[PDB]
Image (cartoon, rainbow, N blue to C red):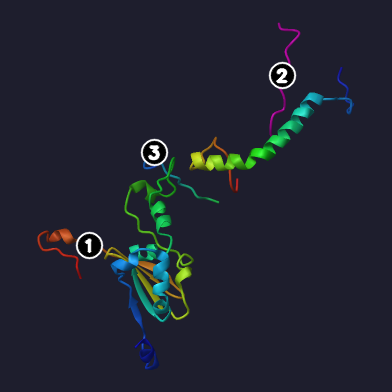
Amino acid sequence: AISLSKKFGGLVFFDLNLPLPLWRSRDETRNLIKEAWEQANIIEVSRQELEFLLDEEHYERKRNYRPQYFAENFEQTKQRRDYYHYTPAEIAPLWHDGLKLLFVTDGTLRLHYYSPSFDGVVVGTEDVLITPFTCDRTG
Amino acid sequence: LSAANCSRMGPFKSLGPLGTSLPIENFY
Amino acid sequence: MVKMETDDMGLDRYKMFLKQYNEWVAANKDRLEKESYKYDQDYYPGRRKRGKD
């Protein structure tokens, strides 16, 4: 099916959505999903999925760095949640020539986008507490 | 006092031991 | 007493110490940097210079 679509002008979107068996190793998964990734033009991955693929522990250590004596920016003076933007070099282990766009999502809170020539983040929000008795995040 | 309280505002942009003194004959 | 002349001074004892120290540095320069990193996270004045420093 992928091949037939490309013949007729199609563009392929791989929304990963990893299943339970595939969360065991980074190595077993990278191999199983490889052919699909390289035949894909637009890809969506979650924040937890992207880190799983590359250096998950390294990212975890980073978010728990609290500076010892003085803060380096006024931002670190304020104790707020982390919203790291992954630099383009970090994602280079996973780029290929036919990738037009890559989206990494952190809930509805942040959406990061990566393109062959540009990068960035779109700010968002979430208010599940406005309706406390009818809230489900399922879809 | 900690980091939450103090911050670095500005990013912006021959020497050694000469010796030890010798005691003195003329103390006065 | 000041002799402006030179070459007659023998700090033999100091010189021997100087050679002695030179060996010491060689042996533990590396150990000493690794130890700093482990016990001291960020440089503040008064702590071992490391790296680009």
Residue where numbered disc 1 is placed: A126
Please name the residue shown 72% across and 13% down the image.
Answer: B23
Residue A133 higher or lower than B10, as above or below: below
Query: In this view of the protein, which residue sits in the foreground, C16 or B26?
Result: C16
Picture coordinates of residue B28 (x, y %)?
71, 6
Residue that sits furthest to the bottom in the current view: A8
**Amino acid on which the number 1 mark rests in the picture:** Glu
The type of residue carrying mark 3 is: Ser
Q: Is residue C50 left or right of residue B17?
A: left
Q: Can residue A122 be seen in this view?
A: no
Q: Do the residues labelled 3 and 2 touch (CB within 8 Å)?
A: no
> Are the residues at dot 2 and dot 1 in contact (C-beta closer than 8 Å)?
no
* Mark 1 secondary-structure assignment: loop
**Is residue A101 shown above or below C51?**
below
What chain does badge 1 belong to? A
Q: Which residue is drawn at 48% across and 69% down?
A: A93
Which quadrant, please, contains the C terminus of chain A?
bottom left
Magenta residues? B15-28
Give how far across and how far down residue A42 sits, in percent.
37, 78
Disc 2 residue type (three-letter): Ser
